Image (cartoon, rainbow over all chains, first blue to last red; front, side):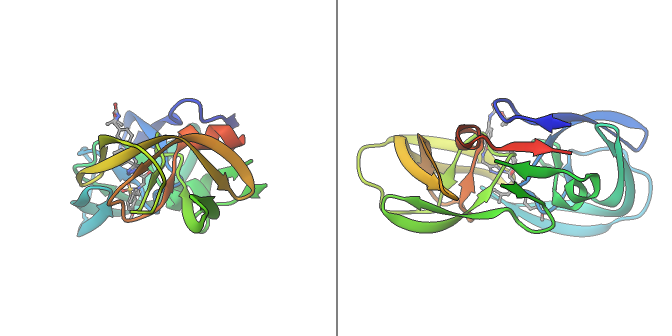
Length: 99
Length: 99
Ligand SMILES: COc1ccc(S(=O)(=O)N(CC(C)C)C[C@@H](O)[C@H](Cc2ccccc2)n2cc(CNC(=O)c3ccc(CNC(=O)OC(C)(C)C)cc3)nn2)cc1
């Protein structure tokens, strides 16, 4: 749908069979989730943010359902203080910015 | 207008008489800009991000022009690696998310 920004754009996601909440984050190239139980293999990774860097695990071709819209793509897992849906998956769901 | 997210949503801003580029960042409550020459008074501040915290200066009722739309509101200044337009100003310009 349409979503205004007077509040945090928080949505429900399903990933790895689990239900979580996450932020629609146009300022994120990438999707980064708190430590979770994800099946499979993964390669080590570093990502930058305000405040410095975190080390994360990069899983590829992960299926994730975002507010009812499915996507498959990279999901990084690690010590992020907030679940973040980044542009790699926002594009897949047809999400746009309008003003 | 409308803006898709296949690339970073970077826009031109004018603030303090200067021209800069910034990210339309739905994942930011607040607007945070690199160190700049802003007129006036300001109170000390801390803000959190991925990676940890940064100390910033909080200027209030700052006028800023964002891609042609004017807003007045809080602008935090500090060691952010990227100029960030947050929800406090995105709401003022009628920016929404759509999918
Ligand atoms: C390669 O791929 C990527 C690389 C980098 C990223 S990123 O680091 O997450 N990122 C870009 C970054 C360089 C600015 C996307 C951005 O949107 C994150 C989002 C973010 C927000 C919070 C924490 C980590 C990251 N973000 C927002 C802010 C500004 N501060 C707050 O909004 C802000 C808002 C709230 C608070 C605290 N308020 C509160 O009461 O509770 C919370 C902690 C839940 C916010 C503090 C700062 N600082 N970081 C993403 C992907």
